[PDB]
Amino acid sequence: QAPIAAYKPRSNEILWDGYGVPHIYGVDAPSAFYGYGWAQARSHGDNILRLYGEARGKGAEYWGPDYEQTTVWLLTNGVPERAQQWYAQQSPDFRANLDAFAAGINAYAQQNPDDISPDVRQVLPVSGADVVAHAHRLMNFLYVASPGRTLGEG
Amino acid sequence: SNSWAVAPGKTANGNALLLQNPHLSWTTDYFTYYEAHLVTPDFEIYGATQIGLPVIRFAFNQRMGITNTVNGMVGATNYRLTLQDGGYLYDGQVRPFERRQASYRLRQADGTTVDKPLEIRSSVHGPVFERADGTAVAVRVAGLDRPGMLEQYFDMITADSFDDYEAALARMQVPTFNIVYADREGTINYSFNGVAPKRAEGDIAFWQGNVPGDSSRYLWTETHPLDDLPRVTNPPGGFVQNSNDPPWTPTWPVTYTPKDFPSYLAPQTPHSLRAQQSVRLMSENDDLTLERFMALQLSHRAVMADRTLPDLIPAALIDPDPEVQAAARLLAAWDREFTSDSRAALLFEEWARLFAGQNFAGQAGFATPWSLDKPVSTPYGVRDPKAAVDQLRTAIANTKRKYGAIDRPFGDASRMILNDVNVPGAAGYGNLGSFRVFTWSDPDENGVRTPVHGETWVAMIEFSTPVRAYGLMSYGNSRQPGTTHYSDQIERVSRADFRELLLRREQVEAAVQERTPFNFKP
């Protein structure tokens, strides 16, 4: 017994629901990823931009002393550079999905600048490598090797 | 976090069941979940992910779905270096550090930046950090060479079959997490996943401490493949679970034991009362419907009361203090559930904080210790009831100070408050036995408290044709200033009134409140 018939989008659209849940319909992969980028930027853009800023190792530069130690942690562990490497090392198809996702964010911000907090404007535009750099911080340098276990603060 | 997958044999209708149930901070920005649905001519994925991630970690669709829990996979090592002559001692000889001169800009009060120099030193292990106390520490993180994390998740969550799923998982690009799988074909899987260094000696505790940084003996270079890791597929028990417990009771009956794996992979520590309930809730129930499966997810038993109050109460009634006596009778009459109307629950929590520590994980108070041979019924009892009564005495004082009374309704102190929404709490601390988790803050001066951590994204999916799923996001789908989609779900959470998750086009169209046409050109 086969599943229900899969849906074939004919146009790129986000149908949002009453709870602000995006249903992103793309005619191909980069399109859906772009929609997804747009949506995430709408619902969470400010904090996403701040996080990407940090994972560039630009926390201290964009936002001063409160962000300095995470900056030292990520530079010392060569995170922003490694993310550029991992980005180049992506498969062509998936790398294109990432560029699209990043393009969605940039496009939402460009079309809706009022929605973007003054303090995170300087981070734009964001790149495929930003997207890889944040995921890399999250998995390896928050989950696996937290600054606390190494520095002995907890 | 909790995770359940249930095989068709254990269900009434003959379709697998899956629970996604991550517990993370309600405030930490990178821990914020977002719910979305992506549809192309070639794939479809529904579910939640941490903000800024382009792939859905908690995904399902018409064919399959997965969920995650923290396993603490030890994928890094911290080494204590022995400094000598500007280098470090290593295999009997002094070895110079690698060093580069980096720099960064630091924003000033007046909006300018200053360039600050940053020397980066490394040993053969990795980058070197100096601790506040002077300890030179080198950190060695495994899997710095797996650029494929996101694509693996992507290929996992869009897998056309379990073999494809397993093939993707086997790439070893996701460095951590228990990961649980289910599908419409009827397969369920549990994997203890991560990128684990192959080491010759040492248990997990050895590898979590400062490993000596003076010998190549400890400088690992290889990591384990997937089939070295604890895994379970379609066990005779008909379910798998994980609730952050060591992977030794992922199902019942178990399919392996700690001896089957290197001792540095997972701890062998007592399983939390929450984890014990997880096993019980699945094993003891059969012929499950999705409705019943949802009802079981809401469990909020004070298992610790079950283990302790039989010894505590009689000992407490012996005490000359009338207020201790009254406290004992209050506890005695309690049904042992974290409900809103409970007059005893707050008092019990305050006693357990002293009995079992602030985290409720302490073991030294129990009469019978935990044993993997009785993994859902130990530890048990009160070892020193006289001491425990003194703890009640203090706890009575603490409860009155924190909450104004020893019998304030649980749901009156325990509120979920987002924007202008303020609703009664139920459930509570995982380590007290509550499966559905709300890690209540310390109270304000009024004795009111709110979840710092707990239920965030919650979904339960039946892999029927079409699939049928329900979910809620505690803190809404948005956090942008002025959004109407921050506090619009917490009221439904207070009543456990789950949204039907909408995957079918017809359903999406019926529910649409906003359309955003877009177009992408690279």
Image: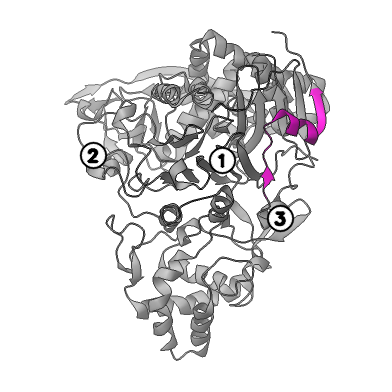
The residue type indicated by label 3 comes to Ile
Q: Where is residue B331 in the image (x, y as percent from the top left)?
A: 51, 78
On screen, residue B148 above or below B47 = above
| Apparent side of residue A92 relative to residue B196 in the rendered image (left or right) | right
**Mark 1 residue crowding within 10 angstroms, few (<14) / some (14–19) / many (20+):** many
Where disc 2 sits, the SS reads helix
**Mark 2 residue crowding within 10 angstroms, few (<14) / some (14–19) / many (20+):** few
Q: Measure the C-alpha gap from mark 2 to mark 3.
A: 47 Å
The chain letter under disc 1 is B
- Residue B279 shown in magenta: no
Check disc 2 and report the residue beneath it: B260
| Apparent side of residue A61 relative to residue B507 in the rendered image (left or right) | left
Residue placed at 57% from the left, 17% from the top? Answer: A129
Q: Measure the C-alpha gap from mark 1 to mark 2.
A: 33 Å
Q: Which quadrant would residue B400 be assigned to in this image?
A: bottom right
Q: Position of residue B100 (x, y in %)?
A: 42, 17
Where disc 3 sits, the SS reads strand
Q: Looking at the figure, which quarter contains the C terminus of chain B?
A: top right
Residue placed at 80% from the left, 24% from the top? Answer: B516
Check disc 1 and report the residue beneath it: B462
Check disc 3 and report the residue beneath it: B417
